[PDB]
Length: 157
Ligand SMILES: [Zn+2]
Image (cartoon, rainbow, N blue to C red; front, side, top):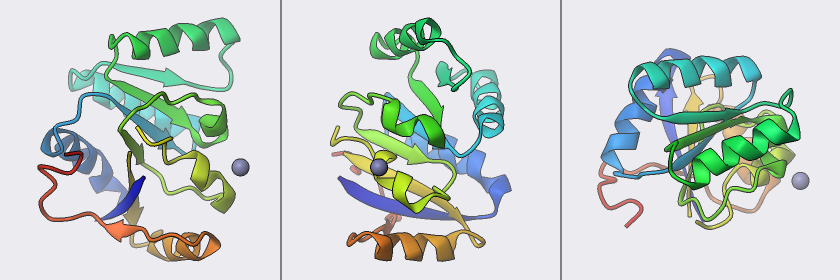
């Protein structure tokens, strides 16, 4: 799993960075994690308005609804699956090649459950306010989270 970060500088630039990235890296399906249900719902709404097909999973969903959502994703009906930090470990991201942390994990431990299973590329969005916490992450683990390259056309090969 290759781990990168994009310094979006401020929360407001995250949405545009996500959609531009989505096009630039030419990926089809991706999983996105946010730290709160509210952010998941808001990002899902914006994405859908922009014509993207998205599925969202929340804790308040009964097992039936979650299993439906997953089938929606696995079949390709939805190109994007968005979930919360709390549900990351319970989400069986298949061999999805791209995972995006729209919000940098606030719980350092949960980070390894938010980077996929090898598809494997994980991209972390950080603002000037989160950059520090990211460094702590690199220490908490013995890994290296590199700044995303200027040219990612061949990112996921
Ligand atoms: Zn764990």
